[PDB]
Length: 21
Image 1 (spheres, rainbow, N blue to C red):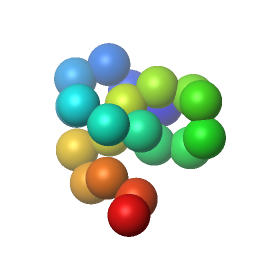
Image 2: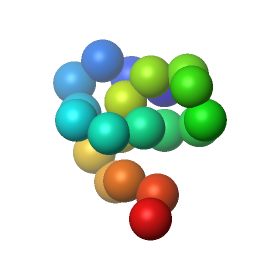
Image 3: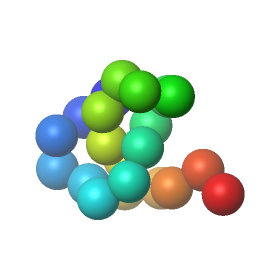
Image 4: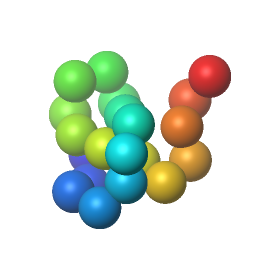
C-alpha cells in the first residue's frame, strides 16, 4: 500500500519494494 515502489502490496491498495510473484 505505499507510494515509492514500482509494483503492488495488497491487491489494488498501492505499491511495494518486495513484489508478490
